[PDB]
Image 1 (tube, rainbow, N blue to C red):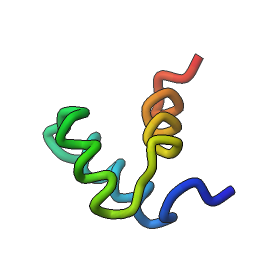
Image 2 (spheres, helix red, strand yellow):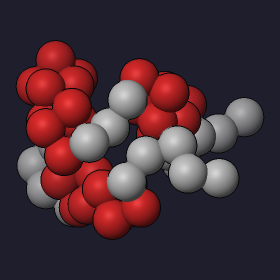
Image 3 (tube, rainbow, N blue to C red):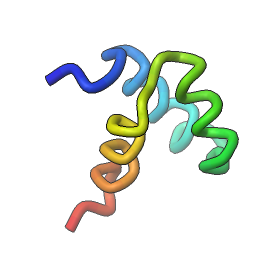
Image 4 (cartoon, one colour):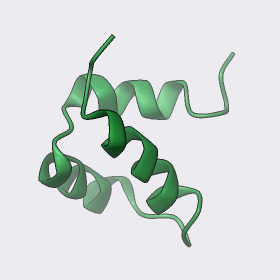
Length: 52
């Protein structure tokens, strides 16, 4: 169930959607800064809110 840092997942929503949006390239750098991994990064994109 832990595929990232709990509070990081939260604040990615803060930084991506709740802000003026951030590019995936910069996002990935910021991801590994807070403690993400490509697993959580894919999760966050594919299952953001465009889920199908």
